Length: 244
Image (tube, rainbow, N blue to C red; front, side, top):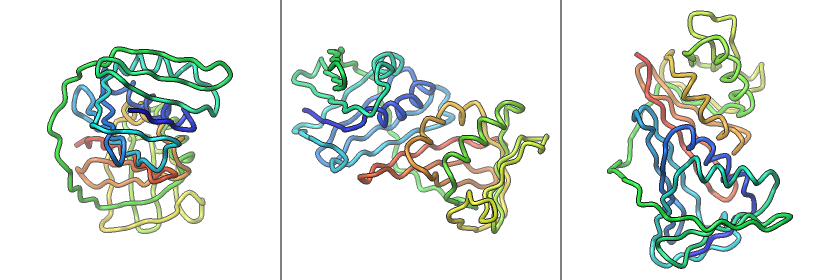
């Protein structure tokens, strides 16, 4: 198998999130797309990735191929990539995977393919009280700001706005609304306010580099979902357990 993607930084952004969450993970190359699902060690959160074949400059898969890897090590590799540069991932033997960053100097790494333990997760039908599409930069700024004063990020939804604020000290508050310009769309079922771990949200902020907007879904005593649509039909979701 062989895939070529035209911007390694996009994959770096995804792998950067994974490296803060789990020691090892598996990219599953299938006929129509590349898939990944990973739970953090405590099973507090879940990242899911689907990259359709149409995103790729070249895409040659015959048998489904599972590339298991250590997330720290793949980061050691992808950290050499600073620019918009293509990445090739290939394998001609089940035990080896070749990663080629093709910039100024083509740098190739022949890594041992790992057998990583996987689990039934099945499809999750989630219901939420609120969903909204908001600015990814605004969201990143809010989480970075709130995370410097509290461990708990309060997310609250109303009919015309999303507020992100520092739990029990609400002088850190980013508003997403049409007035503020941070709110693109809002679906309202019921008023909601719940807390979520700032640590875990900080872990995945590299995902905000994937799209200008993030769709956020949550509810009272419900998990929080982040969803990023990518050019070419790529999809990435992060699901984070609620605080009670």
